[PDB]
Length: 20
Length: 21
Length: 20
Length: 374
Image 1: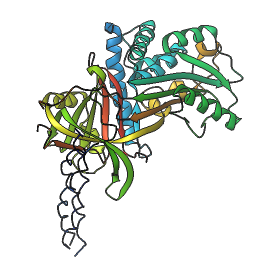
Image 2 (image 1 turned 135 degrees about the vertical axis):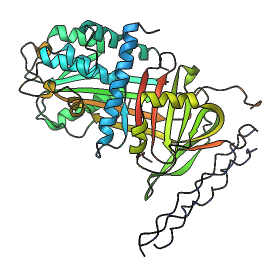
Image 3 (image 1 turned 90 degrees about the vertical axis):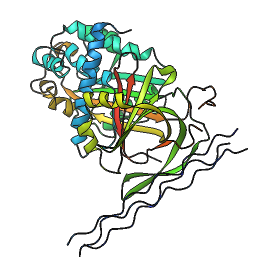
Image 4 (image 1 turned 120 degrees about the horizontal axis):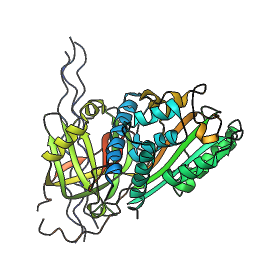
């Protein structure tokens, strides 16, 4: 009977790009 | 009785630009 | 009661390459 | 049902609020925005009601209602104001009060007209007594909003002239309520390098929704109680300043976006709490054409006092916008694993929102949330 949970949090920010 | 877990969350932000060469 | 929060999202995409 | 004159002024007010939004959006000092189009148009109606010659003529031009008589503007805006009062507990509180110096007396005819057409009150304060002046203003707005708007401003900028103060409280009542326990702590990203903790409410149901993959933004329609009005939220795909979205926000583009929407299973997550925004529209209204009304040497507000004593110093637009879970109890959504894999409308970064009347399409609210509070 309990409603489904809320969506999970946002994932981690991506890794920095390679050095130019 | 607690309900089922929620859906997956949103994808994280894109990474910052790399350091200068 | 409401369900627990879902799983965290996938980690973001890698960043763009840096400047030269 | 609105009269055809009040309906034309409803679209006039909506267009005026659009230009107000864009003008304030360029202002790097402006953060959150909250504009009620009928209340903004009422400020120009008061200047036209209490003014003559170019001071009253400019106020009608900024409203783009030149082809209408003066008493048609006051009566039309009067019908529009009372139309929103007949749709309360959504909870909607509104107060309008003119503050003049003690050296000036209000003409009885202007007091009768402004109260009849705009529910406008009138008070005299000593602007040089800064503490007593702010208290008189802040305590009136708090009384009007029952404490939801405890203070308007912290400083009166021009100690001579008139201050038009509007205090508002709005609380959207959803057609489909959120579960009162579907709240938790989430991080709101003001920018990519700035995250403030907020309370967020979550509901998953069937909503009108469109994903613009071309211009990278999401649009969802949240109907209000008994589908008499709707709350539309526009949020970019990436965490970015809303300036790019604001260049696309037009009357034409919004309609195109509304037509591409379709009822889909959508998980909506929004910040929960009260957002307090105070605006001084006076200088922005001048940039739209209301130039003489703010000039202390040229203003003609002689209908207000009898002998040309006042000038428009400030037009305070103060609002308390509460996001809450309360709404109408909906019957089962049992014939709808429909919500098993819903689209995510995860509003943890700045978004643009507007409130639209379903019957007339008139704009009840326009604004944005760039920096909440927790």
